[PDB]
Image (tube, rainbow, N blue to C red; front, side, top):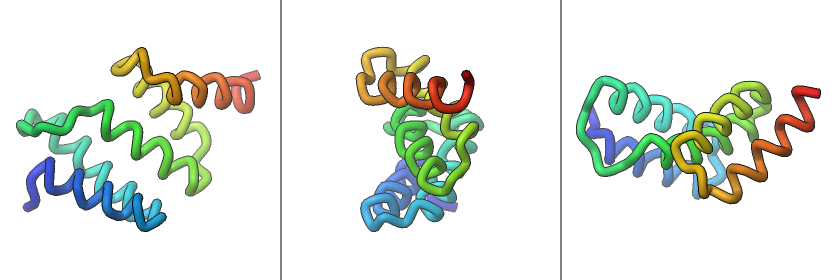
Length: 94
């Protein structure tokens, strides 16, 4: 019903309130619509940034690692995401 960019703004707003569950609900919807080829100004790397932080807050550890890996693949100079990936691999995968 809402556009990709509208849904992204909903997700950003929830994140700023510290509402990580609703951040996930909105950002997951954005990923669906982006994958369906819907046109948007928001990019996938932006979505993965918010979603990986929100799912980490909610305790979904290997999902957060997966999404952090995908974020870096689409945004290799993302210094924070590179530090997060090193954190998660040291913590979870040996």
